[PDB]
Image (cartoon, coloured by chain):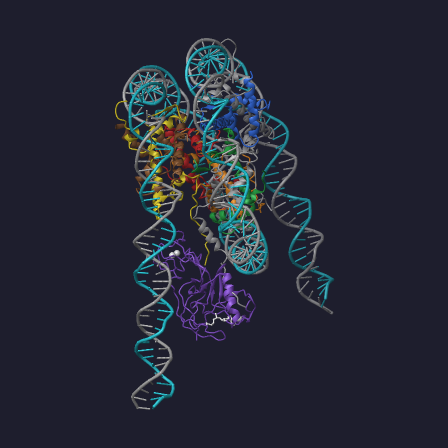
Chain colours: A purple, B brown, C green, D yellow, F orange, G red, I blue, J cyan
DNA sequence: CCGGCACTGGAACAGGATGTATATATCTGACACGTGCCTGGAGACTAGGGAGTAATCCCCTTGGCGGTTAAAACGCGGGGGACAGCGCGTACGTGCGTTTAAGCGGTGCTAGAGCTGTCTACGACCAATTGAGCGGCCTCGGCACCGGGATTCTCCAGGGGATCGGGC
DNA sequence: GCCCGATCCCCTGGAGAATCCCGGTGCCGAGGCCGCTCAATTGGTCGTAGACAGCTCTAGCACCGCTTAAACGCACGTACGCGCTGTCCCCCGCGTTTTAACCGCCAAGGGGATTACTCCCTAGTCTCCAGGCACGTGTCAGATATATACATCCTGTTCCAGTGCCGG
């Protein structure tokens, strides 16, 4: 039984925090052309696919052909909520996705570093055990509390089949989990991650791998 | 102000030759001086080269024939083939009227 | 007032930026002591001639045509200052 | 004089000063005697070579949705035609920047 | 106890391919104006003492020194690639200048 | 076994005899037959003075002999000793002739 | 008009001739495809000079290419040549 | 004339023709009015600059144990001086050969 | 018939005999030193020209032929030739 | 369990055979003078303006001070590109025998470059009258920026119907 | 057997949310309009620079024969390209903290441009005369051609340097 969590499509500030957009005056131009099967595709080279820029639907010379419009077109699988053991509702895919594929984007609540310290020291001490903090930049902290997506709905591991990357679109950063290999359905979905606690460890790393002994705080 | 001395330039001919090619665009104060220096730099080459053609042959006149060879020496392949026609036409148009 | 040491004003990132505008991807650790030796002699072969042209006309101020002429002497023409 | 003054630039059909070119040829110490058809041949060449640059400056200025020329367009206009680039080899234009190019082996490979 | 997660970093060679595409498109100046203006006055105390400059003259040398260095760092790269490398070592600038004719 | 000087020394034994003479090293008639054929495109039925053919041979040889000394530094840069046709182009390109 | 047409006289710059110009320059060992690019480098130097010599001749209304027109055409490209008068 | 001709190149104590350098400046269209201390100053420099390139070619001839100066001696005298090699940078001298030099990496191991 | 052809031969030959008494010089070398002098002459004049024209004057003088030497001759020649010339120009007038 | 009848890798050095200076003769074609004579330098005077020179106004190069925030300096990590070594075989150097144009004496012929005289068309010089061209003044006035009311789209919402565990 | 009091999938009044777009404000940078003055036009006289119809004579192109250096293949074996793998340390990406470039002000004076006046250094014309250019003749400095006298490079035959691996 999932607890009550609010849903939201894209990010949002939560007070003093504010995002910055970008006009079409300095957005980096591509160099491909609307020629073949994959205009600004994945295989065919693209100076924006390489350097971690997501094209804009207008600056492209092809126009309505650049497949590198993902953090906006919102291409996902469905992946109905599955249940795991020892953690919660760890989820299993129901497609046969290839490698280099997109998975849900981590969107939440964006909060100042100083502000974050307060919002965790308020609740943590009252036995809520909040464990959703992921830094993007100094003064940027995406929080998965008040709001969220299918993105908060993830699980740590040590030998995963997906990772956390970092793109930038329209002048602002993004975070999108990707497909590292061609994983079929009937497989658990998880991503390892590195952290740096402010208090102490509370659980030895427990994944189910061969060398996944670890801890919570060590690499 | 003592009504300072005057200064001459190509700033009202560069601007005229613009409107016969692009009847809508404008030009900036900092991209005018570049064309000014451009003309005041391509003038000396074509003058000085004829000033030595007219000396290797023991003469003292700069005719309308030295300028037709200074061009053929200074300008590259396809450029030096239209300027010749421009010149030889704008003098036939002048010698009659 | 006297001066010294001011060649250390061409900092490290100031050379990295001129490099990136050139088109180089990685950079060794000893270019930063070789480029400040290439830049310090190109300047003398120009300031000497600027000072000479100024010394000739009995002035006391390096105007902005002396530099154009000193650079025109060596096939480094400059467009847009006079 | 008696009759009306028809400027010497108008007869030939130019826009450059055929009156002023003559004085500069006469007071520059290039010879002892200057002909009569020299400035008319010299101005009709200084006109063509300015048409040839303003044309390309406009053609490469409208490709950015602007209606005004700035020093960057001049360099982009000249560094791409292989005859103006040869006639203007050792020349440095202020506030011009470089052309866009990266080598072919520095692009990250698969 | 209450920690924070962190995403990956960039594989070496992307914040260096962004700077190229960013700098080959603007037109500003790339050296600090006062530090450059003091070097010019420090050099020129060896030819004639107590001479002044013109605000538009001290900015005439900076538009040439850099168009020189940028054209030299383009011929260093061709040699560094000739030797089957990616890095540019000091023993390339000397070859470039030697062939060109300065030394 | 005709005493077989070890390969790589006869060359070093004439590098130091062609650096002291002053003669010219191309055949006069096969050179003067090339000039009269290149210059047939520009103007028709010319006649060359006899001291304006010997005035081109020096320029041509003093150009090639000074291009090879700049080719022979690239081949050393790349850790070789034999010059190849992918070197001439680098020297010309760096000079600024193409 | 004895202008008996000519064909392929570039192959007169033979192999040992090029090797001698090489040896004078100080090279120890030579590849096998240089003898086809040295000709292509020479036949482009000669034209930029002969064209200018013929232009200097035409302007004077003559028919004999003398030995001062070559000196002028060479001084034109920053390749001054001492020795032959001027 | 009243007195006898006391030529101008002997008042200054030179060797080059002051009477000729002046006319050359005048009939060559370099400027309009030519001064009177110009030819004296220029002929002296022309004399000094040629009073040195021979002083080295002579010293280079006495090493072949000869007496007559030929072109090769001039090239060997010029390519070995750090100032003349900079003033005559782009100039070629007929019949001059090259300057004897060989690399360091090619000598037999 | 064969009008004439002036040169600097009889003066170079006079200069030679002050630095090397017993020495001769062949034709191919006379015909080189000739062009050398006849080349330096025009480089030195053709810049006093442009100096006089920049400063808006009409006369060439010793104050021009000096500044035209510090720009052409590099290094120590520019320090010895200048010392040379201002001896002849001084001695000439005082006569 | 390391050493001993013979046993196998590195080192040394005269000795040969070739190429590179020595000294004698010897001889020839170009270097260094002497001679006449025709230009071009030199010596004196006269007449007109370019540059040395003193005095004046005022533009613009220094000198100093304070606050902001964009950039430079330093130390941790941690993964990727430079330098060393080995092995395999393709390609240029060396020498010898055989085929082909460069090169050196002439000899003939005429095409075109250099000179000389006559003489007509053309650019410098000068005075007079008037229309193009630079300096300054205003105006507009297309371009950046916010109110700003509301317009397709999207929730929060408490409640309208479909539904059940026994209720009677 | 027939029926009821709340209770989960749907439904739209409040709202709400950014946000194409109609519509206020302020620009520093260019764009059109009048006094003002001086370089360009026109009309005439003159004295040369340059075009041209002969005319002599040097030299660049064409032919021929002959003796010999230089280009041309052809076979071999070796010294140098080229491709591949393993160890490693050096140059790149981040987080904190320190500093001095920058924008924007006030204040004092050095020296850069002009301008009116008076002298003295060059352009210029005649006569007058000697330094330098072509011609013609004499003889010696240097280029061959031999004949030695070596100095440089290459390789096979002993001697150290430890010895193959067998053993009792
Ligand atoms: C983000 S929550 C997701 C909960 C549940 N899996 C779901 O889908 O709703 C992940 C939880 O797994 C726990 N976790 C993460 N890594 C773990 C590990 N290595 N061993 C045991 N628990 C772990 C964390 O404490 C955290 O509470
Ligand atoms: Zn693309
Ligand atoms: Zn795109
Ligand atoms: Zn684990």
| Ligand 2 quadrant in view | bottom left
Provide residue I80's location: percent of width, then percent of height: 57, 27
Provide residue C38's location: percent of width, then percent of height: 54, 42
Against C13, is F50 above or below? above
Against J89, is A79 above or below? below
Residue F81 seen from this side: no
Against A174, is D3 above or below? above
Q: Is residue J75 left or right of residue I32?
A: right
Closer to us: A94 or G43: A94
Against G41, is I8 above or below? above
Quadrant holding the N terminus of chain A:
bottom left
Number of dots carrying numbers: 0
Quadrant holding the C terminus of chain A:
bottom right
Provide residue A162's location: percent of width, then percent of height: 46, 66
Q: Residue at 50%, 71% (x, y): give it.
A: A128
Q: Residue at 34%, 25% (x, y): give it.
A: D35
State which quadrant residue D74 falls in. Answer: top left
Residue I8 seen from this side: yes
Q: Is residue J88 left or right of residue A107?
A: right
Q: Is residue C34 left or right of residue F30?
A: right
Closer to us: A35 or A145: A145
Provide residue F13's location: percent of width, then percent of height: 57, 41
């Amino acid at each position: 039984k999932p607890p009550p969590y609010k849903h939201i499509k894209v990010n949002k500030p939560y007070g003093k925090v504010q995002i910055y957009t970008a006009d079409i005056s300095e957005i980096p131009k591509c160099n491909c052309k609307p020629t073949d099967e994959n205009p600004c595709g994945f295989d065919s080279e693209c100076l924006n696919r390489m350097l971690m820029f997501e094209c804009h639907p207008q600056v492209c010379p092809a126009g309505e052909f650049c497949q590198n419009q993902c953090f906006t077109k919102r291409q996902y699988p469905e992946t109905k909520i599955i249940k795991t053991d020892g953690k919660g509702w760890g989820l299993v895919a129901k497609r046969d996705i290839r490698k280099g594929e997109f998975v849900n984007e981590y969107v939440g609540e964006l909060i100042d570093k100083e502000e974050c310290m307060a919002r965790i020291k308020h609740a943590h001490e009252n036995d809520i055990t909040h464990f959703y903090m992921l830094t993007i930049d100094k003064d940027r902290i995406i929080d998965a509390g008040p709001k969220g997506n299918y993105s908060r709905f993830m699980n740590h591991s040590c030998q995963p089949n997906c990772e956390a990357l970092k793109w930038t679109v329209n002048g602002d950063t993004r975070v999108g989990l990707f497909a590292v290999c061609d994983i079929p359905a009937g497989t658990e979905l998880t991503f390892n991650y590195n952290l740096d606690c402010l208090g102490n460890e509370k659980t030895v790393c427990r994944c189910g791998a061969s060398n996944c002994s670890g801890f919570l705080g060590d690499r | 102000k003592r009504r300072k001395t005057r200064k001459e330039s190509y700033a009202i001919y560069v601007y005229k030759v613009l409107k016969q090619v692009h009847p809508d665009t404008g030009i900036s104060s900092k991209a005018m001086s570049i064309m000014n220096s451009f003309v005041n730099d391509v003038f000396e080459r074509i003058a000085g080269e004829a000033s030595r053609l007219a000396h290797y042959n023991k003469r003292s006149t700069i005719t309308s024939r030295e300028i037709q060879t200074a061009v053929r020496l200074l300008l590259p392949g396809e450029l030096a083939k239209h300027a010749v026609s421009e010149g030889t036409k704008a003098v036939t148009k002048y010698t009659s009227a | 007032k006297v001066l010294r040491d001011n060649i250390q004003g061409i900092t490290k990132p100031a050379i990295r930026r001129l490099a990136r505008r050139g088109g180089v991807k990685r950079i060794s650790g000893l270019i930063y002591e070789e480029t400040r030796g290439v830049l310090k002699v190109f300047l003398e072969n120009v300031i000497r001639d600027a000072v000479t042209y100024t010394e000739h006309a009995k002035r006391k101020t390096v105007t902005a045509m002396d530099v154009v002429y000193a650079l025109k002497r060596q096939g480094r023409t400059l467009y847009g200052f006079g | 004089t008696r009759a009306k003054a028809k400027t010497r630039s108008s007869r030939a059909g130019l826009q450059f000063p055929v009156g002023r070119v003559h004085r500069l040829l006469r007071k520059g110490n290039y010879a002892e005697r200057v002909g009569a058809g020299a400035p008319v041949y010299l101005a009709a060449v200084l006109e063509y070579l300015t048409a040839e640059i303003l044309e390309l400056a406009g053609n490469a200025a409208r490709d950015n949705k602007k209606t005004r020329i700035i020093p960057r367009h001049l360099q982009l206009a000249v560094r791409n035609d292989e005859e103006l680039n040869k006639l203007l080899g050792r020349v440095t234009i202020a506030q011009g920047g470089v052309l866009p190019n990266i080598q072919s082996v520095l692009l990250p490979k698969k | 106890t209450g920690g924070v997660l962190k995403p990956h970093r960039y594989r070496p060679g992307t914040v260096a391919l962004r700077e190229i595409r960013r700098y080959q498109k603007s037109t500003e100046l790339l050296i600090r104006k006062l530090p450059f203006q003091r070097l010019v006055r420090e050099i020129a105390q060896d030819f004639k003492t107590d001479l002044r400059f013109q605000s538009s003259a001290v900015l005439a040398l900076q538009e040439a020194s850099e168009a020189y260095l940028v054209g030299l760092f383009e011929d260093t790269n061709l040699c560094g690639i000739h030797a089957k490398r990616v890095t540019i070592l000091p023993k390339d600038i000397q070859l470039a200048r030697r062939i060109r004719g300065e030394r």
